[PDB]
Image (spheres, coloured by chain):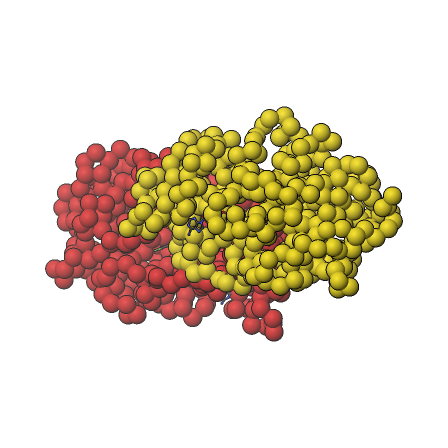
Chain colours: A red, B yellow
Amino acid sequence: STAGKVIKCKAAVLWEEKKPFSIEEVEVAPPKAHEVRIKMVATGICRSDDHVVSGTLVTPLPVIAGHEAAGIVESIGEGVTTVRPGDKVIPLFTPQCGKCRVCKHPEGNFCLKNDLSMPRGTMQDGTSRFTCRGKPIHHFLGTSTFSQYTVVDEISVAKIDAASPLEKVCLIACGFSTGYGSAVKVAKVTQGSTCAVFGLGGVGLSVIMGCKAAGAARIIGVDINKDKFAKAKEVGATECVNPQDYKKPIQEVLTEMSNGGVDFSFEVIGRLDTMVTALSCCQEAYGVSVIVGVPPDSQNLSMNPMLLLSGRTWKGAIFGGFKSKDSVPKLVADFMAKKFALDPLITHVLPFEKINEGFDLLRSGESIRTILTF
Amino acid sequence: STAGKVIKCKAAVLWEEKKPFSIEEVEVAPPKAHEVRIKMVATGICRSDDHVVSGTLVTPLPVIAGHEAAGIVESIGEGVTTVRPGDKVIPLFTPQCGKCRVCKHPEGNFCLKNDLSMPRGTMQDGTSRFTCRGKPIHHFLGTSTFSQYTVVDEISVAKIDAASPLEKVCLIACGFSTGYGSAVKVAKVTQGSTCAVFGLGGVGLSVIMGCKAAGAARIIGVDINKDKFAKAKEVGATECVNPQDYKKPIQEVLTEMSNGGVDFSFEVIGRLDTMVTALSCCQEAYGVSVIVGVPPDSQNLSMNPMLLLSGRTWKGAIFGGFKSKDSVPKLVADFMAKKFALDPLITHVLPFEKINEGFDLLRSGESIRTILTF
Ligand SMILES: NC(=O)c1ccc[n+]([C@@H]2O[C@H](COP(=O)([O-])OP(=O)([O-])OC[C@H]3O[C@@H](n4cnc5c(N)[nH+]cnc54)[C@H](O)[C@@H]3O)[C@@H](O)[C@H]2O)c1
Ligand SMILES: NC(=O)c1ccc[n+]([C@@H]2O[C@H](COP(=O)([O-])OP(=O)([O-])OC[C@H]3O[C@@H](n4cnc5c(N)[nH+]cnc54)[C@H](O)[C@@H]3O)[C@@H](O)[C@H]2O)c1
Ligand SMILES: OCc1c(F)c(F)c(F)c(F)c1F
Ligand SMILES: OCc1c(F)c(F)c(F)c(F)c1F
Ligand SMILES: [Zn+2]
Ligand SMILES: [Zn+2]
Ligand SMILES: [Zn+2]
Ligand SMILES: [Zn+2]
């Protein structure tokens, strides 16, 4: 009945930086060839969504943000083969076109169709499916999950288990998979190792979960908000440190604590200074440091390349290094089989209409993940 | 007999920065416990030695530099078990104590006993075995090979094949092993891959040799001195490019040439700008860049961490990642077994007395390695 028709629905439109979202009617065009229109069920609030508001992340405005979500297919465009109406699906903010050199590479996941490197805020065809007040509205990362209905390219959606609890597994769409993969896949954390995790939000807690799953003997959480330490310990941190407690720089503190540097460190904040501090605190000859946090737009860090010459490895990743369409259904299956927990990341639940309250909770420091229900 | 006695011999003393070496008589103390006194046979001239002269590398002066050499044990101190008088040996500018957390680590080589990070210019015991005109003279990296005789700690020497041609295998002490291992061990170059090698001196040519040995399909040499290209092709470069020939930055040229970025890039120069160019020219999702070149003292580079967040790996290494005492004898055995060639690296052979002429050949661009013979 809605197939092939424009849908009027509520979305959270961001008209301007540093402003509340406006919950208002939008028009959602039907899907074109190899497009999928989804009725959203649940979306998380990730700090990257907040980066759009703050201008830390630059993407064209006005926009419908949101990238951490799950929903139910309303309709498919011509030529779609991988989902059907009524399927539970996760929009993939990192696409998997399956055809580019990255998709073909055994270790690549940052598909060349992404809209992250140089955001256009469109569908793959360079156009928008969203109208508000008669004006075209940008997409975000090909997902735009802050809407009762979105339209995504086929390469940006994965079918997931029909018995999935969508209010939980939406976290597999970003924060859990990112943090857990950054530990298990990107860093390849080893049994008995010492890890340091900078930033104890949803993503950093997910890194801790991955380090614990990998067998790390010591997992040191690092946050300037000590209110984050209890949850970090619950999911596997062996100890937590607040840089503000120490006269010396925290890289020196962590080097002392680890008797000469940690095996694996993770930047899970988004600061240039903590990206360098995290590199420095891993052991100089064999340490590995993984950048997870999103840096501020167009800003360069400064570092001494002797940190690398001695033997350190420095790397970053999007989405925990997971090939998105292959991995999201497997992660959902593994969650169904209790191979990892998502509840420790969910601190608050709100209706979608209380999105601004959700962002207030993240900005105050209170929440980890707020899950919004449509 | 010289054993147990001071030796007066000839050495190349560097009294201050940016001056010629002084070829003159020094006194060489006998070895103390766990020390080895070596009659030098051949030493290479590595750019790192020139860095001490130029002040690119800071180490206490006055100094007997030189770190790429081979010789014959003259005597051993109490408690030495791994070499004997008459043995061919290579001094190890990266030690292998065998006891430290790095030496115990399967992928560590930068032994904590090294004299690189925070150079003291002494033996392990914090004293010098060298005097000249009544003045104590510093060691360099535990090796000091620009002397007819040196004294090294046991952990800084490896016994090698008695039939070794020391005028060739001296290059296994630094430049060959560094470049080859940087490709085969540190980058882990894959069969069929595309490599970019920045700097086509002795070390960069050894990187090419390693990339070819690893089966790379394409090996692009990059140098501002086109006179370096012919020998780069001889040892495996498939293409060579001179940045000065192009209007665009060379990272853009190399990304275009490799249809979206190289698999593996290597900085083998020692410039901050080429370290960032080399990182940028590797494919953004799965590329690997290795820093080999020694950066100038205390200078930071500037870079955009989005280069790593997309999926790049950035690493560095000393001595090609090789655990020095285990590896050197095996590398010399492999050379003896015709597994790789060293002659392509040797452009000049001079008496030791012509050390300054050897440095002038390096600085002018003419030479790859000059071997000095005692
Ligand atoms: N690479 C990816 O694919 C990916 C995915 C998801 C999130 N991100 C980014 O990862 C970062 C973390 O996201 P999140 O967990 O949702 O955010 P969050 O909940 O804001 O957590 C960040 C944590 O960092 C802490 N913090 C802030 N400053 C400092 C400091 N100077 N030192 C130590 N701790 C500090 C802060 O108190 C908070 O608990 C953000 O930059 C995201 O944009 C990246
Ligand atoms: N990591 C290690 O363990 C290790 C070992 C040995 C040498 N090194 C360092 O490796 C570097 C190379 O040593 P080497 O091969 O003996 O030196 P080299 O023979 O002087 O070779 C350097 C090459 O770089 C070329 N070059 C200079 N500037 C540029 C530029 N802007 N762009 C492109 N090419 C340029 C130059 O023409 C020359 O052919 C030096 O910095 C050494 O100190 C490090
Ligand atoms: O949180 C995931 C995430 C990222 F990791 C980014 F690098 C990015 F630009 C972005 F928009 C995003 F949502
Ligand atoms: O060429 C080898 C070499 C290095 F790689 C250094 F980092 C250094 F400091 C040095 F003195 C040296 F000789
Ligand atoms: Zn792709
Ligand atoms: Zn996110
Ligand atoms: Zn050691
Ligand atoms: Zn050298």
Residue in the picture at 28% in, 50% down: B247
- Residue drawn at point x = 31 percent, y = 35 percent: A99
The residue most toward the left is A134
Q: Nearer the viewer, residue B245 or B27?
A: B27
Query: For the point 29% across and 50% down, which residue is it?
Result: B248
Q: Position of residue B212 (x, y in %)?
A: 48, 32
In percent of width and height, residue A330 lies at 43, 38
The quadrant in which the C terminus of chain A is found is: bottom left
Question: Residue A154, percent across and down?
Answer: 27, 40
As drawn, is B248 to the left or to the right of B116?
A: left
Q: Is residue A106 above or below residue B302?
A: above
Q: Position of residue A24 (x, y in %)?
A: 21, 62
Q: Quadrant of residue B163?
A: top right
Which residue is nearer to you in this view: B75 or A97? B75
| Front position in the image: A217 or A110 | A110
Q: Is residue B76 visible?
A: yes
Q: In what quadrant of the picture does the N terminus of chain A appear?
A: top left
- Position of residue A234 relative to residue B77, above or below, is below
User: Is residue A157 something one can see in this rendering?
Assistant: no
Q: Quadrant of residue A17?
A: bottom left
The answer to whether residue B233 is above or below residue A208 is above
| Rendering quadrant holding ligand 3 | bottom left
Identity of the residue drawn at 61% across and 42% down: B350
Horizontally, residue B176 falls left or right of residue A361, namely right
